[PDB]
Length: 212
Length: 223
Ligand SMILES: CCOc1ccc2nc(S(N)(=O)=O)sc2c1
Ligand SMILES: CCOc1ccc2nc(S(N)(=O)=O)sc2c1
Ligand SMILES: [Cl-]
Ligand SMILES: [Cl-]
Ligand SMILES: [Zn+2]
Ligand SMILES: [Zn+2]
Image 1: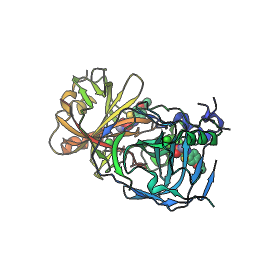
Image 2: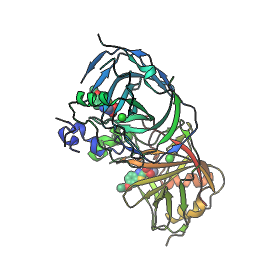
Image 3: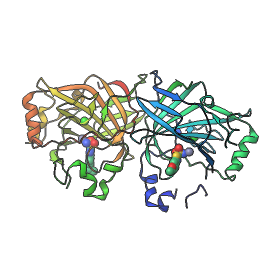
Image 4: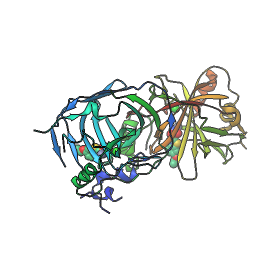
């Protein structure tokens, strides 16, 4: 059984062999990239939303097909949000104590994932509805203006399927220290961060968008 | 047994011939593709060429292409990492399609660095003027005369850069592609001969599935 306990994922199932063999496995440290000033091309179609279900090695909140992201002429339906502690993706070796992943699928079956860091500070109201289920302020969840990193990668969890479009947001969200240990407690006080995977000089663009 | 013919050994079946080749199917950054969506970028000038005229170690037909091997004298520098041009080979038509445009021919500059990491540079050809750069080879397949590598490429190039795979089995990924937009020119006769030297047998992998590849457009000076 696969866990984060103390590189052998490929062994447990042959379905997981790509975890080693893939040349574009995630997460990574974002250190070399291209600046661009091209249109967002990223449109959010988010609303405050109450979960299809809320359940637990990571804390996950799933949703109905109500929230969308449209990228270069294709609609990606929001499936779920889950957390990693520490932040899996590194930005020039800076990681945040917590992260969230927003998972999407298009007509063609393609995957798009949204990642953002958290900053230890003020209480974050967006977390509480989940922590009948209370609705989550998605369209308000995200920063107004985001600087993001976009590149190609894999699932950070098995089967580590690749073909994932990652957009990693620069801005850290804020989380209070009680909330942090609580979710950390919520995840059995067991870390669920895959280490940085081998990076074969991934082509990375830095760009921005308006989430709302 | 892989080939480009429509029988059991074509591209739609390359994954079946050897288990070493399955990434041809399962791989998620498979090349070639149609380059139409990309990001325009600051021209930080990432790529530096260091080519000289060079005589081929060998010029020979292998695995459907005309290949010219070289001593490790011609190089490319990318973000402070140097890749040695290993060989130049040909595909007809051009395999990468640029904004849905297909060219009669392309040339691939295969580079490998110390780590065994791969870099390939592609430039297309369309029918026109006689190319003196080409002729050493068409005769050389039949010592070898040197190739004006330093003179081969356009002075300033527009190219697309992304991560992809090899276009022939084993279809290895982690390949850094530099696809130059500018077409070089070839005479209609030279064109017909290259195809004859490459046996009038197509050696173009079809466009492969695209998983939203991040492509940047930039430019450089080859001279
Ligand atoms: C039905 C199985 O769905 C799975 C399994 C692993 C997995 N990892 C992500 S992530 N952390 O965004 O890269 S999403 C996902 C979905
Ligand atoms: C080890 C044998 O060398 C091989 C096998 C396939 C292959 N495809 C290219 S290409 N068409 O530039 O992407 S180069 C190359 C070298
Ligand atoms: Cl993350
Ligand atoms: Cl090509
Ligand atoms: Zn995740
Ligand atoms: Zn080739």
